[PDB]
Length: 247
Length: 254
Image (cartoon, rainbow over all chains, first blue to last red; front, side, top):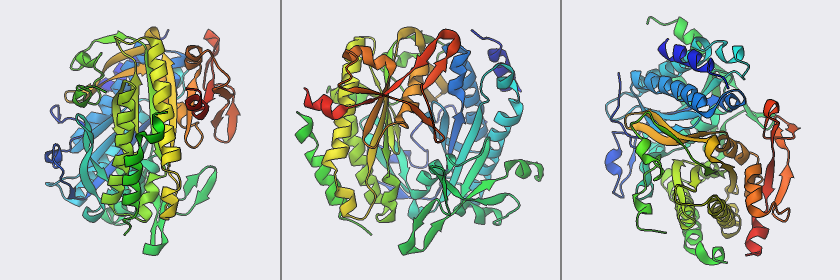
């Protein structure tokens, strides 16, 4: 409520913490920095995009836009922290988050990521309802892409030079999490095939979605026929997820 | 010019990797998310208005590398492209603000740099990056059975009053960054570029004699339709145009 109240107040101005975790340095792999080493290890990759914030400039000055957007981003960061996510990178209009690590089970990683995605979407969709429309600006909404990559498919390593560097992954499923982020509905979440087995492949929460590409549709997000690899993406019903939960 | 031979080792490295299918001593000290002119804003509630050139560099089709290559080879290829891009930006006094998996965010300008110099640096860096990927990596990926990789660059200039530097995030989970229409519009225009193309905003043109030799006005594409401006605020009579930047002819005439 505090973030939503702050945002409402700012919109009236028309013209569990992890404070020591640095960016670009997942704690399970930060030791790879300043070395030439690398490790294969599973991870859940989540890309969060905040859409329509640029429209804020039509009615608000840069300082108010900064307050609104950084408030939304703080809400997102704290949501991720609550569910043991590591914030890897800050975009202007979103976040890159890893779930999992050396002391986390793959099931726990997936559950954490799904809960964090549901809560981020809830905050932006519901707790900020009508606030932007009431002020004559476009509604701000989120898009979240989520994927799971197993150890053999997820390479942790150094990238860059000097301090212009990060410890990050090279993995098809990190890339596909980003791609599926672009595929989501307003305040929606899209997940890859590898997420489903960790939630009993429930068509209760997951609905197969065709991959949209320049006004046309394709059956898969990614295809390697030589390996019989046909990767599907699925809309994640996070609202039904939240309602049908004990907590 | 320089670009014709600058990247020979990077191109050779990438060819070698593709055969494996299944400016200053303190630039090295520059952290991400911490432009040297504004890094002091970290851990503060302070902010400063100051111009900047915002550049977004996107590398497209690199995910296709996974169809034929293992993660370590994909990493070697992408890190080579990234290293060439970082060194290019440093040569033209760019500050690398953020590393993506498939691109970079770069600022040009700062407290001891003229706006003109910032724009010139950014245009030359964009031209050199585009030259490297389009020409020195020509055909290399197709020879090995993967899709051709190309770049897209969006460039914009924001003046002092329209560019707010401030802290974002909390604790160490933070960066010093800009809130500015023109940073956002540089990001937007990046998606508007042609393959190996550069798209710039209106504020870039006066710094290059608005030469239609180099700049071609282009409409903004959005869900199969076209609009005249990247951004419009009618109440301020603000109609912001985007332009293709002919970097090849730019390089030719230097």
